[PDB]
Length: 50
Length: 50
Image 1 (cartoon, helix red, strand yellow):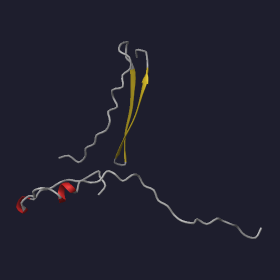
Image 2 (cartoon, helix red, strand yellow):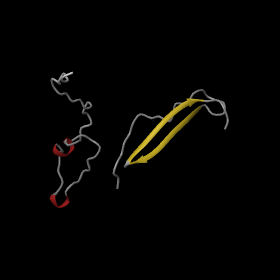
Image 3 (cartoon, each protein chain N blue to C red):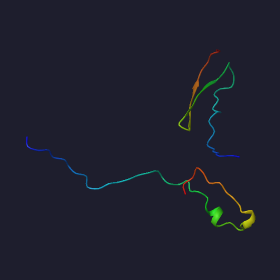
Image 4 (spheres, rainbow over the protein chains, first blue to last red):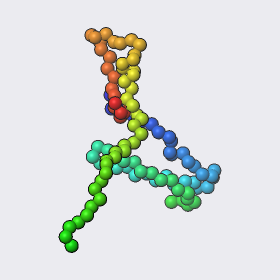
């Protein structure tokens, strides 16, 4: 039983550089309101642990 | 000050998006072979413009 399906251009993989702690912060927000499922995103450079 | 003056609208326009995600009715009205009435075929249509 499957009541939906969807596809689009990928978003997760936009890594910068090669080494050093972690390269790019991925930020997502998921919210389920009035049936709709809303997904917001952003990607940002960063050089830091924790 | 006796009255008010308003430039009434000449006409009315509407603009919705490019109307592209057409439903696949061709796969149901232009299929090479149909199913038997005792075993009718069923296709689910969703998330498309019919």
